[PDB]
Amino acid sequence: KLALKTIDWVAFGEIIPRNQKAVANSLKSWNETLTSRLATLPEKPPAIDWA
Amino acid sequence: TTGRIVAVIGAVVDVQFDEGLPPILNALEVQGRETRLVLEVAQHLGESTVRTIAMDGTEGLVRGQKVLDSGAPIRIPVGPETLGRIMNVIGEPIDERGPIKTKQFAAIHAEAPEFVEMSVEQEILVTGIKVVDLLAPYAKGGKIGLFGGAGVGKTVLIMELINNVAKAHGGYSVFAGVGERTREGNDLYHEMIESGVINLKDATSKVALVYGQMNEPPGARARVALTGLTVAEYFRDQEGQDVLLFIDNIFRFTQAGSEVSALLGRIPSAVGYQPTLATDMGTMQERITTTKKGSITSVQAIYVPADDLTDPAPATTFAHLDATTVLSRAIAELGIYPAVDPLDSTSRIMDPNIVGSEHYDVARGVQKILQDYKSLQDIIAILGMDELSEEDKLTVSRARKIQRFLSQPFQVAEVFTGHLGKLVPLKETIKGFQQILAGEYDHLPEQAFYMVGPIEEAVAKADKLAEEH
Amino acid sequence: VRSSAGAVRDAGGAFGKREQAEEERYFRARAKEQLAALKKHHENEIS
Amino acid sequence: STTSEQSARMTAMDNASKNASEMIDKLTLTFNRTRQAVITKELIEIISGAAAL
Amino acid sequence: AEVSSILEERILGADTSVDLEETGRVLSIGDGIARVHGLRNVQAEEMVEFSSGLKGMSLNLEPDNVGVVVFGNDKLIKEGDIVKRTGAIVDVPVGEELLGRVVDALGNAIDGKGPIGSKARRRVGLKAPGIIPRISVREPMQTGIKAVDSLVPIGRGQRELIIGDRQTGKTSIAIDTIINQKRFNDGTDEKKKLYCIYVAIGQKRSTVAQLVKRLTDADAMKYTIVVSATASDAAPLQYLAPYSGCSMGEYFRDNGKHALIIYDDLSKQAVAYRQMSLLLRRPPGREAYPGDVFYLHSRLLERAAKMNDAFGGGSLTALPVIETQAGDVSAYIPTNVISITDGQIFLETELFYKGIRPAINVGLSVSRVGSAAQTRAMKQVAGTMKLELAQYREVAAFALDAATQQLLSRGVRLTELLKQGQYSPMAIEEQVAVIYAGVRGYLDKLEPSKITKFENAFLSHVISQHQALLGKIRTDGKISEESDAKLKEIVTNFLAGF
């Protein structure tokens, strides 16, 4: 299901023109929050004891 | 004689005798207990009743239980067979190694030596600790105190002394743990087994242990000191030999005495202490003495409740000691270990005619410089160091170097510091402090002197600090 | 009730910590200077 | 500058000494109250123990 | 339908046997203390029972009457009542059947959920283990707080003390310790599983309910017992709850397992004991506490031992909680318990409000075990951290040269590193990673207000990308050279990428 391509960040920050850093930092932060959320959620929904 | 429990209140048991009463301080044995419960008579209440303090838990006692009168005070086994063992207040062994097979039993209550038996000779006992040897030197046959609150180094210092003096001491030794953590008792047992003073195979043990730890009811804590003292007294007299006697703490004896006084019907004294505090402590500390027949070197750890040196218990204990080393928390916070306070420690032999004029002058110079430093610290709190007379900065620098140089690494505090223990001969300590005062080191930085042995080690540490600068 | 020497650092209030720091910073500086001089002397005395 | 600085240091030290004096007065009052309270507390403890036998 | 059936199932099995029992008449009942007359063979601190099914303990054996303390309410006992001796010293149920159950000081289920299936009973007043059974403290007790696991470590068999003022975060430390043990209890090896016991003394029932629901949310009642003697429970119950809980933990340590007990507070057991002693007419002492107020605690905290391998190898850690008044550690009960326990953890309100939470005062907090009972990685890193904070605390009161400026910078970075949230204990390897990053000059570039952001993001990144490295550190239990090189490259990459 999930296999996310790895990233280099110091490399990533080399490719933002000064006029575009204001969106690059926001994208970084949004990635951070979403990754923390994904880590928060469990690998599976827990089972149910129907019987 | 046979009597009969008639009341049980806490640790105090009232026993009624139909035949003749037993004298005060006698030991009585309760009949019907799986273990051995021994009560000690403390009062005659009239109407044939006697009040007693139980040397064990009074749980499961029934009004009416028969009691036997041994006819003598608590008699403990004494002799060379107690060495390497452990004991209760009542002398039964608690090392799970079998009965103590002696021919002599000694009662734990005895009169103190009379005035015509006192030795009046003093000679320094070199312990290998810089602060102790310099400012408050000990003495063979003298009673030493180690005051200080909780967490300042009393137990570590006493263990260090056992490591140094006891290991290389020909005579015997005794350790009476009074009302201290049982963890520490086990740790000491195993450390002694490892070192070799306690030999479980041969009959070459050099230490006899007595334990009355803080899980015991007050009756047992108030008497384990007397049990250890009895073992030491026998080794002093019959063996006719030098003895050491370590106690930790001798404040739990007083405190345990205070936990039953209110139930024995006595009005309390100054601060919830028994009215008989000074007399009860004197009748014990007066048997720990170097008579002309033997010689006991007594080291005592004395808890000071809440660092208050004016509390009645330590305040009274002060008068029974030749040397004192008042460990201080304000110095242990600084990291100077042992935290012995150089200005609040004293010794009787600290006179120019007993130690020498060089030793005495060095000690007094150190104390004076430290007191001047204390006086200056008030000014530095307002001016600042930058505004002191160029002579004062010299005093402050010397004082800080001397403050650090009194710190020393013990062989038993390897776990905490990670350093290696150093033993500093007395001449080296005198030389080090005389040089530090004379100014022969006013260029090395302060930290070079922190936790080192002789002064040359401080020079080497400074050299290393400079090289990796 | 009186006052005694070395009481400002016995209370341990604000003045006590302030004085302790005013002392420690100064003597760290002087220790650094003395260590530099010690290194210089070491190097200059090898030969 | 040095003249003005010395004048200002004299004034500042005088004011600091005055403030320390006011604080000493207040703390002496508090100390006396606390000393009396401690005497009373210890004495009442002794009395209660004596009467509770 | 079946509701009444199961109702009958209870009657079907009853207690037919009526025996000839010794008795006594209540001469005088008032304030919770009865003075029975009779009971000529009643033992000391034995359990007796009243005509209404209410229990009590025969504490005073005077020649003319027996002073009994009632384990419950007192309005139902009249004069001329009947007290029957049960012929058994006070004892409580013990066993794994109690895990996950809230029970009162006497081992009665308090949350409904049926009865306790305990097959064994243990006497509350049992002597502590001797000198020979014990063995020096070896394993580490993982608390989950960085500042406790790093600077004031706790072993298994140690007796730490959490001492502070009201509302500084003591129960929070206790709950974090309880919750952290979930990772070990879920695993397979039984040498790490630690069963937790929480004795709640004098706390209002609402607080204990909040605590129990908090443990349930973290799924931590699988292995927790809660012995609640709340404020409305007669003093003879708040006096005895610590001993009941300590017996429930003595069972575990005597059966080769490991237990953790948390008395909370002991300063309220002291008050309950004082009330009992004053209502039995025993003379008061200092601050009105009885003379036997040190004994009360020393006999209780001396049962937290670390048995050697001949006696099972089990252990029982204790974390008593004391409450000082305006930081007056010099008070009576605080000093007693400080001189009883091994370590201490000083929480200070000045640190709580200055932003340092947990408020642990690392300057004064101590732990005798220290070196021992610490994992090798933590031992390696926390040592340098301890030295750095020790140096920082000296020059801190102000705020020039490069060396001391960087010293203050490092000290502050480490300080903001040690902060933490609530009920989020960390695995030891994660703590090692964070402390290593902080102490190896890496964070010295960052601002000190952003260190929390780093800590959090770094944890989230490592827990997923580099789970293998954390597993390596945990399994091998040290920062090997290859592990150190990895840690180095991960931190160097992450710092720039943030």
Image: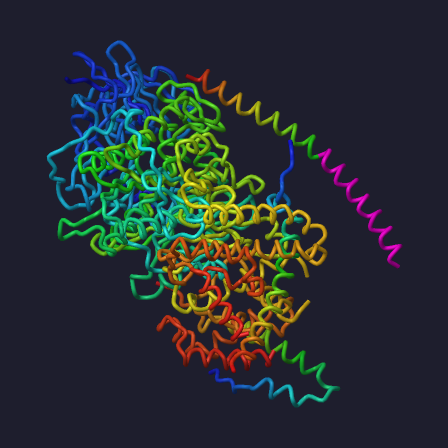
Residues in magenta? D1-26
Residue in the picture at 45% in, 22% down: B269
Res E115 visible: no
Q: Position of residue B345 (x, y in %)?
A: 47, 42
Q: Is residue C20 magenta?
A: no
Q: Is residue B374 left or right of residue D25?
A: left
The C terminus of chain E - image quarter: bottom right
Q: Is residue B115 left or right of residue A22?
A: left
Q: Is residue D11 magenta?
A: yes
Q: Position of residue E155 (x, y in %)?
A: 37, 56
Q: Position of residue B160 (x, y in %)?
A: 35, 51
Q: Is residue B210 left or right of residue A40?
A: left
- Give above or below for A45 relative to B123: below
Q: Residue extending furthest top? A: B47
Residue in the picture at 60% in, 68% down: C34
- Give above or below for B422 relative to E87: below
Q: Position of residue E298 (x, y in %)?
A: 37, 39
Name the one closer to the observer, E151 or B308.
Answer: B308
